[PDB]
Image 1 (cartoon, rainbow over the protein chains, first blue to last red):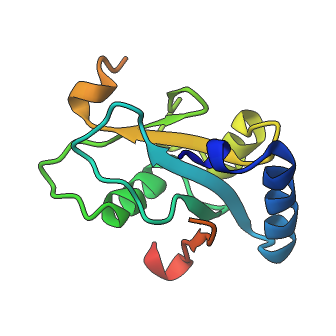
Image 2: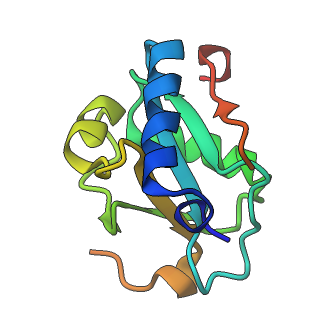
Length: 119
Length: 12
């Protein structure tokens, strides 16, 4: 099951309250496989704490390594249901504008054919 | 899948 399917809203909110207490400089992000994607693998851990200074292109490099991707394997992130406005956008800005009601920032990843047209 | 994966600066 996906994260939201496994945890109730109240449990998600409490997860966020506690984790943000414990990690004063990290953003809580859920990073899951796009439903329908079957080239890229599933992560063993899909709950992340991301240093709050990074930008999206830094995060992409990290998640490609987490997935142990080859260089010839395409990867794209959708953040809160849309493509990233820009790879240079700080994750602190992304969190403030795109976070869920529950306090997590949600993303999914996909390969080229699954992701489709990029504009 | 309940434990968080912590990204650190030593990775950047």
